[PDB]
Structures are given as structure tokens and as C-alpha cells.
Amino acid sequence: VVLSQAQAQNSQYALARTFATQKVSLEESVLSQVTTAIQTAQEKIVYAGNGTLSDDDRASLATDLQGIRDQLMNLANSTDGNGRYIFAGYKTEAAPFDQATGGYHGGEKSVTQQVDSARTMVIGHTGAQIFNSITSNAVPEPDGSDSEKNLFVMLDTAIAALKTPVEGNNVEKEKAAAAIDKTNRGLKNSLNNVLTVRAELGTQLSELSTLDSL
């Protein structure tokens, strides 16, 4: 009895595993795209650091950035093949991020799944974890204020700043330039956060395959 039984318990963990592997692989694929998108915005933000840019050049950068922001929003709202949202924790049936502000509305608890007697492997990192978090490596705000954690806020503030024509207004220029500097720090912090998650999903995939190929 205990044999058949155990062999059936390990037969079941085998299924969880197969479910876990497809879920983690899609997340990893989508996060790979999130990385490239943020790196693209980072390049525009660096260009925006140039003090002699035309207001029309600045507005152009804002438009490029709105586009990247919109790609990232679509990635943050990604679903799997059954239309369940992958960055929403357990709340898989409503979009985790609102279009207007990029606020997170999904679940807070990470999705877990029993993989082997021993472990309880975290599957499905939540939206908060990817798009609204920073690691301990985060570059702090020079002025001691709290670091922005929400990627969409980082992008949205920069966009609003760049769309503000600042010709002939040094005060507005310094303000907008400070917003761009803040976004620059934030995007490094966001990139580091996404890189951290991707590495951890890589580990998860490695584990799953080590029990799957086992």
C-alpha cells in the first residue's frame, strides 16, 4: 500500500511540476521582454539628460517613452493560453494593472505549488514583485526621500516632464530635469529588480527540470 501510494504521490507531484514549468517559462519569456523594454526606455532617458534639447526633441522623447510605457503595460497585463493573468498572484481573472496609472490590483501573496514532499515552490511571481519592487541594491534618492518603486510612475512622470515645453523657463527646465534624473535612478532600480526575478525563475526552471528529467 505505502509503495503504490507513494508512487502515486510522486506521480502527482509530477503533474504539478508540468504545470509549474509552463507557467514559469512563460513568465520568464515575458520578463525577458520587460527587460529589453526598460533598457530601451533607459536609453531614451539618458538622451533626455542632455541640457540643450529642443522642446520638440523633448516631446519626441516623451512620445517614444509613452510607447515603451504602453508596451510594458501590455506585458504587465500578460495572460497565459487560457487568458489567466500571469502577474496577478491568485487573482487571475481581472487585469492586475490599471491602464491610467499603472497601480497594482492583483494578489499580494505569491502563488505556491507542491512540487515534492520536501518543497513548496513559489510559482507565479506577482505584479507587485516585478513592477512595484526594488532590491537591497537599489540606488537611493540623493535627497534621502523614498525611492519610487512603481515602474509606470517612473515612466509617467518623465513623459509628463518631457511633454512640458520648457523653452524660456529655467524653473520649469530644472524641475523637468530633476524628474528625468529621478526616473533615471528608478529605471536602474526597476531593471535590477526584474533581473533579480528572472534569475530566480531561472533557478526555478532548473529545479523543475531536475525533477522532471530525474
Image (tube, rainbow, N blue to C red):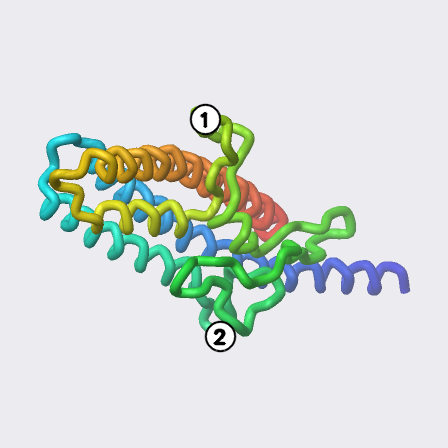
Residue that mark 1 sits on:
143
Residue at image x 28%, y 53%?
A: 68
Q: In the drawing, what numbered circle is on residue 82?
A: 2
Q: In the drawing, what numbered circle is on residue 131?
A: none
Q: Residues within 10 Å of mark 1 (few under 14, many from 20)?
A: few
Q: Amino acid at mark 2?
A: Asn
Q: Quadrant of residue 89?
A: bottom right
Residue 47 lies left or right of residue 10; in this view the side is left
Residue 12 lies left or right of residue 156; in this view the side is right
121 or 94, which lies in front? 94
- Note whether residue 18 is visible: no
Secondary structure beneath label 2: loop
Structural distance between the alpha carbons of marks 2 and 1 = 46 Å
Can you name the residue that lies furthest to the top here?
142
In this view, 27 is above or below 204: below
Q: Amino acid at mark 1?
A: Asp
* Circle nearer the N terminus (2, 1): 2
Secondary structure beneath label 1: loop
- Note whether residue 15 is visible: yes
Residue at image x 31%, y 59%?
A: 70
The quadrant the N terminus occupies is bottom right
In this view, 81 is above or below 117: below
Q: Position of residue 121 (x, y in %)?
A: 66, 50
68 or 206, which lies in front? 68
